Amino acid sequence: MSSLLNSLLPEYFKPKTNLNINSSRVQYGFNARIDMQYEDDSGTRKGSRPNAFMSNTVAFIGNYEGIIVDDIPILDGLRADIFDTHGDLDMGLVEDALSKSTMIRRNVPTYTAYASELLYKRNLTSLFYNMLRLYYIKKWGSIKYEKDAIFYDNGHACLLNRQLFPKSRDASLESSLSLPEAEIAMLDPGLEFPEEDVPAILWHGRVSSRATCILGQACSEFAPLAPFSIAHYSPQLTRKLFVNAPAGIEPSSGRYTHEDVKDAITILVSANQAYTDFEAAYLMLAQTLVSPVPRTAEASAWFINAGMVNMPTLSCANGYYPALTNVNPYHRLDTWKDTLNHWVAYPDMLFYHSVAMIESCYVELGNVARVSDSDAINKYTFTELSVQGRPVMNRGIIVDLTLVAMRTGREISLPYPVSCGLTRTDALLQGTEIHVPVVVKDIDMPQYYNAIDKDVIEGQETVIKVKQLPPAMYPIYTYGINTTEFYSDHFEDQVQVEMAPIDNGKAVFNDARKFSKFMSIMRMMGNDVTATDLVTGRKVSNWADNSSGRFLYTDVKYEGQTAFLVDMDTVKARDHCWVSIVDPNGTMNLSYKMTNFRAAMFSRNKPLYMTGGSVRTIATGNYRDAAERLRAMDETLRLKPFKITEKLDFRVAAYAIP
Amino acid sequence: ILWHGRVSSRATCILGQACSEFAPLAPFSIAHYSPQLTRKLFVNAPAGI
Amino acid sequence: STMIRRNVPTYTAYASELLYKRNLTSLFYNMLRLYYIKKWGSIKYEKDAI
Amino acid sequence: STMIRRNVPTYTAYASELLYKRNLTSLFYNMLRLYYIKKWGSIKYEKDAI
């Protein structure tokens, strides 16, 4: 659904068509003007950062594994005559429709008997999904993956690509897959009895030399070398695929460009009348196009074990019954062609729709992981109460759409209760300790991180014990639309730390809430604060991120009693464009204000600019008003004359309109 | 007789034994003597038996 | 209907006898007995019993 | 809630017999007993006590 994913984008964000991606890492964000203030009994110290960049790093790598599951049939496409008043295939009108058609008379009785089983095999989501992945593999084919590269680095702990993804050879995305071609046979119209467990599709005119090569590779096993997101492992959809094309199927060309895959999709959707099938495949790919680079070192627990992708079995019986598909189809919603029409016009817009969906999910799974099991709406039972339909199993797209509904605070409506795609809530529901590997840089690591060893020499491979999952992404596109006090994503905020002159700089935060806001605002001001817990004896640093520049309470890496000693004569100025706290006395009052917002994207430590035309909000009415218009100007070549007009020179001629 | 779709592997064994002679050893009430109903039974199933 | 056209005249003649052969009571009776034989199959009968 | 509609007659027949005997109370009973054996697993029973 293009419509619901479009509304997630911010108001200030004005996207263009083309986006020239030339790397496997993008820092999307915005530039804002922060007017910071520090008030005290001595006086006020004002600062101003005119261009403050708040970013979330997003990569094109992520371990996924496809499995073939059984899903509901999508009945949108079949002629409206055979359907009854309630909206189910009234068998008796099917036998009537087949009898009054251009079918062979000896096949009518035997084909009608099979109809009861074969007409309820309508799900082309798996085919469209694979054909969409082939489009983006050939478009962004020049992106590279190095084996010994830095997945994450925060100064203390480092995590390499070798650690998370073993059995991984370095190669380009184009050179990753070597897809073998499945057989594309021609359906004989005079076949005695239809062959079930072999799908048959429709086609307009002649199957081109390149269309054979695309359909051949789409219905085949994906066995990748490099762990890419749009080239993950998928099982063999089918062995053989029939195509009811009276004009013969040309043999396989071998080569094809990304423009030829768009040609193949547009013919397949139009012939089969499968637009709702495409809408399902569009939302599936939106989840599993890009995966987020973790905010903290201990936020890598989400991507340790491979999340399963639920691909519904390829099943289509249109080739055997050409009569039942015509120009008057049955559809539930009137805006059922909107998702395809959006993709054909603006293919590269999927990148923006993808980051909008994963940012919405991973933000909400952040503040869902911090609720006790003894509650009404908890970790296990947040999907059941929200869903008001009848899906087969609460997995895939249902779990991701219900998280988006919680974030935006609106009602998401789909025409069919389809349960296909990636399932994210895997590591959460387990409710056990996860052992993430790490290579150390400094020697004073295991004070900060909950490490397995207490003394570790530099360059050693250690393990961190993560119990509660910290947030993987900070809200950026969904900044101050549905604000919570955990993230504290306000435009205006203030904190009041109360100290007396008798205290020699040392302040104890009994409250946990205002400790979080103090440590966060001090980092905007470019000050390196290092607090020490009095009960346990561990240490926390506000500088625990190089992207957002905020301090969340989950950076403590421990749930206990709150007694944080901060010594305010060991505060060090780290960044540029900073206010100085030289020697405070009395009550401190910190405050900031974010005024304006400008969309910015970075890649390879350089600005990535959006190019091409101005993207519009395509509606169903905007095309069918031109159908209402029809260009009703009678196609008659009316040539109008020009009267020559003489003036002073007479050498040169001058023509007038009347 | 008529049938919906395909006659399963077990449905053949049940219909085969139902249309046969009951020759019991012990005098049970639900296993009394019955003659052979029929020798052959046709099934109009386009999907093979 | 969806019948073979050469069979219509010969099948219609037979209809007078064959359409009045409708009694499946004997088949259902035997199939019901097979259900209960396999369900309560472990019951025993002794020859020299009271 | 399926595409393969050949298995519906078979599925219904088995489901009708099994749904009228569903009970997980005995499994949870033993799982609860295993929890408290591990937790309070340092209690001594002496045979020649009062």
Image (cartoon, coloured by chain):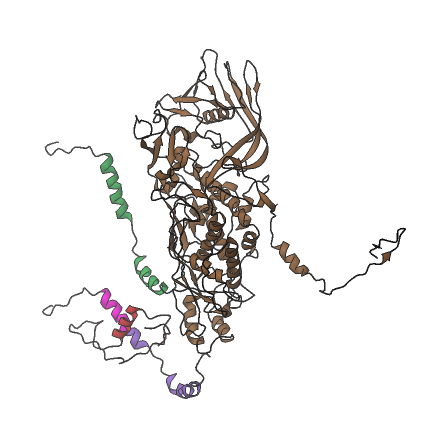
Chain colours: A brown, B red, C purple, D green
Q: Which residue lies furthest to the top in this view?
A: A502
Residue D48 % position (x, y): 10, 32
Residue at screen point 42% across, 61% down: A315
Residue A618 % position (x, y): 60, 51
Vertical side of D11 occupied by B20: above or below = below
Q: In this view, does A451 lie to the left or right of A630?
A: left
Residue C37 % position (x, y): 23, 68
Q: Residue furthest front?
A: A651
Residue at screen point 43% across, 60% down: A216
Query: Which of A179/A191 is in front?
Result: A179
Query: Which of A297/A46 is in front?
Result: A297
Residue at screen point 47% across, 59% down: A74
User: Is any part of residue C38 visible from this angle?
Assistant: yes
User: Is any part of residue A370 visible from this angle?
Assistant: no
Residue A536 belongs to magenta span? no
Name the quadrant of the C terminus of chain A. Answer: bottom right
Classify residue A316 by image quadrant.
Answer: bottom left
Vertical side of A94 occupied by A649: above or below = above
Query: Which of A604/D22 is in front?
Result: A604
Q: Residue furthest right?
A: A648
Q: In this view, does A630 lie to the left or right of A60?
A: right
Q: What is the count of numbered marks? A: 0
Residue at screen point 24% across, 41% down: D33
Residue C3 % position (x, y): 44, 81
Classify residue A110 by image quadrant.
Answer: bottom left
Query: Which of A385/B45 is in front?
Result: B45
Give the residues drawn in magenta, as a range. Answer: C30-47
Q: Is residue A163 left or right of residue A347?
A: left
Vertical side of A420 occupied by A157: above or below = above
Residue C45 belongs to magenta span? yes
